Image: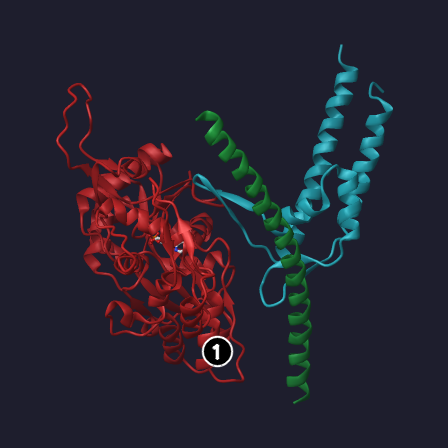
Amino acid sequence: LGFTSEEKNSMYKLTGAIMHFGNMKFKLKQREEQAEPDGTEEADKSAYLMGLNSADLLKGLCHPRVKVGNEYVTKGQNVQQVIYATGALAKAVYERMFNWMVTRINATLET
Amino acid sequence: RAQERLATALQKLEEAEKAADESERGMKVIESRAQKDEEKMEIQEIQLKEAKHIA
Amino acid sequence: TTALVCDNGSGLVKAGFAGDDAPRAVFPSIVGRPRHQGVMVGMGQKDSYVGDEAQSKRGILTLKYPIEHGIITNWDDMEKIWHHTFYNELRVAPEEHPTLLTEAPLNPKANREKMTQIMFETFNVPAMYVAIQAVLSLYASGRTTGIVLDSGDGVTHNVPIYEGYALPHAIMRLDLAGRDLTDYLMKILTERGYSFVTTAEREIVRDIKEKLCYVALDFENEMATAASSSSLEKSYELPDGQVITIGNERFRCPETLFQPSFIGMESAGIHETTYNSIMKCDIDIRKDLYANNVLSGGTTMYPGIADRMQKEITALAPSTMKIKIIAPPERKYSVWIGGSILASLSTFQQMWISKQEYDEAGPSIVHRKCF
Ligand SMILES: Nc1ncnc2c1ncn2[C@@H]1O[C@H](COP(=O)(O)OP(=O)(O)O)[C@@H](O)[C@H]1O
């Protein structure tokens, strides 16, 4: 099909990253209701695959920032919330890659 | 006068980068101390729960 | 169709649409009017600025707040505030949107009645509803049980709730809040020679408070350390210069919440009214209430207030009980979050006050089962 070998390579690695999302581990904090990661190895490897920073992705999962008018304030998360977010992220990236693959297929077919 | 306040701006830049490197080194040592403190406080919170349970 | 969620409060209007994670329009609830002469012909200047526009022209206007302590005291100004919120910050036609409004517990009845009368006659909404702020804080907190302390800018209150049932006889309301903290900080800044008297300098003092003040864990030891060392001194740069140096009044200001005798009030601190609401509740729910003490509102945003309140409530309550204080980072907007959640609930769509109900029953329909 019309697409290169690097592109198949990226497809395979992206699917492997989706697979690496599942083993993440989060714990509640000391005397609070905030989620913090205890295991970091799968985080590091999933970031190295995805093309992001590991500390940065962990911070983006534990502490989302939302827009209130003209400012940004950090939102709090617990383990259930961060797990639901991880699952929704994986489902989203998979479905996105799928739709774009179909677009590539149609572009190859296009006359 | 331009070179005068220029030299003062440059010496301010020197001492300002001094203050900045002090800020960064201090925050490193203090985040290490912090993480140590939370390790200690969590282990002692669990030990407090153990103690009340034995009580 | 979508509902609007306008959380007025006393000093910060924040509005948006039901079903979002945050308000899209947050601005002060001030109405400024020019107080000087006006010389340039053809300048075509207006007569009253509202919202964030009035903050850029503080040096020319006299700033009014239309809401003193929860209560609305200037209905013309409030109508201007609402018009601005609907048409200039949000850009929506309020005749095609239900509107959810909030108010504090234990306010006058005419406040609420006149509010709905305005919203139906002037702005012509299809439906509307007024909600208690503490209940919405509890929605946004993800709980159904807990005692919520909602310190806004004009009013502080506790509202204990258990399994979704609110205990009205244990509701406490206190008229000490951020506005009184600002006035006290203006009064004690004069000990070092700074004087802020203008309504436009009140805003400078409010920004100082927000950026520099914090709650001390131990007030006497912090006073001693401020007297001895100089490691607490912090500087602030006014809109011009003459950087001001602030010492122990960094923490003497918000300590008024725990010692209301500082501003000559008779009542007790927020920790003690929280504990009193607890002991006012039943006995079978006090453990859950101790374990679900929820903070919200802007005046709960000082560094150290959660730890201080936990220390105090723990010293008050019995030793066998575990006290817990829930203080999310998005506390300032909790009432709005909860309002959005509630208005998006599909069960709620039968709770609106429709326009026909109002037309047939008068503004009295608001205290009725249509709450
Ligand atoms: N970071 C902060 N630290 C201390 N006080 C704050 C902070 N942010 C806001 N405030 C105070 O909170 C008040 C606004 O609270 P808000 O949630 O807007 O209540 P309302 O909406 O009822 O006016 C302001 O008077 C301000 O002084």
Position of the N terminus of chain C, as image quadrant, is top left
Q: Is residue A111 left or right of residue C203?
A: right
Q: Residue at x 66, y 75 (%)?
A: B44
Instruction: Write down the chain letter for disc 1.
Output: C
Q: Quadrant of residue C17?
A: top left
| Chain that the image shows in red | C
- Which residue is the extreme one toward the top? A111
- Which residue is the extreme one toward the right? A5
Position of the C terminus of chain C, as image quadrant, is bottom left
Give the residue number, with chain letter if any, for mark 1: C314
Write down the colour of chain A: cyan
Residue C218 horizontal/vertical position (percent)? 45, 73
Q: Secondary structure at mark 1?
A: helix
Q: How many residues crowd around disc 1 within 10 Å: few (fewer than 14), some, or many (20 or more)? A: some
Residue C353 horizontal/vertical position (percent)? 31, 50
Residue B31 horizontal/vertical position (percent)? 64, 57
- Which residue is the extreme one toward the left? C37
